[PDB]
Image (cartoon, rainbow, N blue to C red; front, side):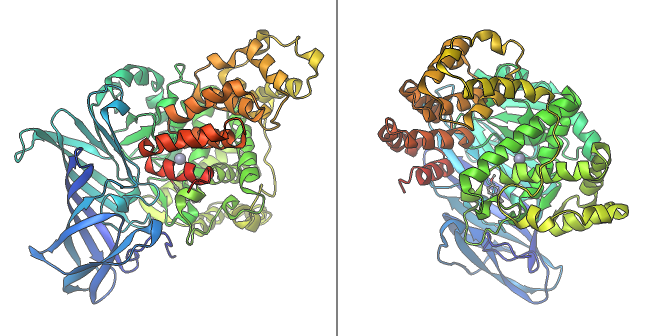
Amino acid sequence: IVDTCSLASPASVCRTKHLHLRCSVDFTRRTLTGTAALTVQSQEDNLRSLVLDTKDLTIEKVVINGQEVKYALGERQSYKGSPMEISLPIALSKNQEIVIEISFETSPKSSALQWLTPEQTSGKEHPYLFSQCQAIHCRAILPCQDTPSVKLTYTAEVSVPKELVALMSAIRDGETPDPEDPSRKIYKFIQKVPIPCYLIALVVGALESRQIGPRTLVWSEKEQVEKSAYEFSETESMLKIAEDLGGPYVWGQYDLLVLPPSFPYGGMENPCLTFVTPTLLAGDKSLSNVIAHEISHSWTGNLVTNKTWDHFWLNEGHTVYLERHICGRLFGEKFRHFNALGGWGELQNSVKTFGETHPFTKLVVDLTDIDPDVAYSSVPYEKGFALLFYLEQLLGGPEIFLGFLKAYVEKFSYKSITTDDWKDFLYSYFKDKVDVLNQVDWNAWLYSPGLPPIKPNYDMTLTNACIALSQRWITAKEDDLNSFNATDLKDLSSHQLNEFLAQTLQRAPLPLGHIKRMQEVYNFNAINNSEIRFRWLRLCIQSKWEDAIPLALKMATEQGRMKFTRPLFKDLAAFDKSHDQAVRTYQEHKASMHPVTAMLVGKDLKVD
Ligand SMILES: COc1ccc(Cc2ccccc2)cc1
Ligand SMILES: [Zn+2]
């Protein structure tokens, strides 16, 4: 197996067993300066040199056995960064190990980091830093074998201003005043469980905590600590359910971190410290499905990981499957089917957006000369789940397939696998149903673009109310607009209301009078629920309602979740009345946007 996203030496040549990170965080220069001690094991005889992944890194020196050795940075290869060859002071035999201390310093243009000014935070007093290494941004923080095929434990000592707090994707290991600087603190961290390097995370800021479980603290600025602790109160309940589905939780502590609005994703599953968007603070725990998702990743993604990014569906596909199983335990089987069916609708949207023949709509992709951030979508999430949901109904139901999953997690625990690894074990587990498995169009499910060859069976109980009301609006005439009222939503949950907008959005645009009437009777402008508002504003913009232009521009910039920001900007760019505003608003905010988010929105707006 070849990782076409990495320029480092493959796992067949050498493997990094441990990392010791000793660095200091300079907010004045916006740089990370320190040393990275990599314990590397040779996988072949007579190993004299190895290559590492770097990206906008400044290398001072390389120390092995107390003496400096010769190193060389090759030319940059765009998004992959610059390869770093290191000359070993001794030829290594197989399984032989050495420790390599690399003195490095990050660039302010680190694609893995976003530096926030005090004004960009809640407290307005202190600066802020958070990392995002998924998929291949860890090289922009430190020199490494930036590949998920290599797992590694790590320890870290991080120096930050004494009035600030540092947190990493590891177990907290005490804090002390910096002996070299009285104005700073040193936070120590330890990760005893081997992780892929993309799971390395760091956050520095005026953070506070509040315990909500025996092994869970919620971290954020003081302004959001209390709201977050309430919003995520179901965390421990979800952990207990997840443990019952995938086996014991092996990370010891599961803390949550609520980041500033510019956090690119809904959630990052960093071990011991899950990163989440503040747009989950709906006030009624209604977006806690994301928490169940990130929790589930502790088994599918963190324990059994994809060997390359071509098999990324292994991570999210199974994780969504566990996620919706957790919500199934909490709110019933009909609720699980509700989210499952809605997820198919999301798959419909992604395929239609890319194209029926677009390579990014394949379950297993080919990221050769392809920036992973560009290819990222809901396809591996939903098509992956669609396959597993299809296999569930095909092999005897949920209880039986949940048996496979637990065996699957235990079989490939602490290991990196491929799709064929998964498929072979599937046939191995269900050996008495190989005739059933052979009826599966594997080539279409795994390697063919567009919608899956077959649609799973979904319960329609909670969805019927959505379809009924949406069809009313879509097929509505002018003398049907008056009969609409606020009573139409009396028996609709927040999820049903959101699905209603999702269904209606698929047939956008609607007549402008329909949308105006909809605001008059439903008052959707008053809803702060990010998911509901996002689809409501998209419906308005696509239906050419100029009144929603400042509202869409506001939400697109007051938060940075690419799930919301990117479709909002594109819709605003497709609307002639707001095209100039959209491009201008982007240009005025791009310097302060997340580096990855700023790049992608630029491509979407075609202002690159
Ligand atoms: C969340 O950060 C990322 C970005 C990109 C990838 C790679 C990928 C994307 C889509 C389909 C298959 C593989 C993985 C993680
Ligand atoms: Zn995920």
